[PDB]
Structures are given as structure tokens and as C-alpha cells.
Length: 50
Length: 83
Image: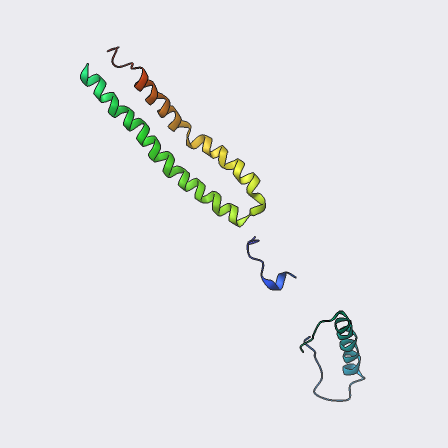
């Protein structure tokens, strides 16, 4: 209803980890997906803040 | 006859002047809303501009009747005939 305003968020990494051990490689499996996506951007040439 | 003529110069001035006053204020109100609508919805301007001319035909309807009668009393005179 307000098309005249187009907030930047609507036009063209936060990482969560545990504080205790005993996990079944839960942190590793995500940290293995964080590294995979970061690679695509390093190949494309972009920098990354975390 | 001199009064019958002189009061038609004032009649013409009222008839055109009050029409000019109303039409000039009326388009300020209508046109100000056309610019407000055009800034809000740039993609609707082709439609809004045509709708403004529909309203403009009603706004000037009586003003043009007044100008027509005022020119009639200026180049012809149904009053000087004392008829």
C-alpha cells in the first residue's frame, strides 16, 4: 500500500553454536556448511564478515 | 440609455471575474491532488491524467457559460434595445 518507499532490506553470516560439549558432531556439521558456502563467495571474489 | 450601457460593463466584469476566481482556485485544489497521486503511483499517471480531464469538464462547465454570456453582452446587447 506504500510502494513509494522501498526499504533497502526489501531490495537487491550469523552463526549459532553450543556452550557445552557432548554434542553428536552438531557444531562440526554446521561449521562444514559454513565453510562450503563461504567458498562459493571467495571463488566469486566477495569478502565475508561474521 | 447611458445607465443601461454603463451597468453592462460592470455586469461583464463580475461575470468573467467571478468565473476566473472560481476556476483558478478550483484547479489549484484539483491539480494539487493530481501531483500528490502522481508521486504516490507513477505507474497510474496515464489513467489519473485522463480522469483529471473528466473533472475539468465539470469544473469549467458553468464558467464557460458565464464567459459566453459576457462576450454576448459585449459585442451585442439585449439590454440597450430596452427590450
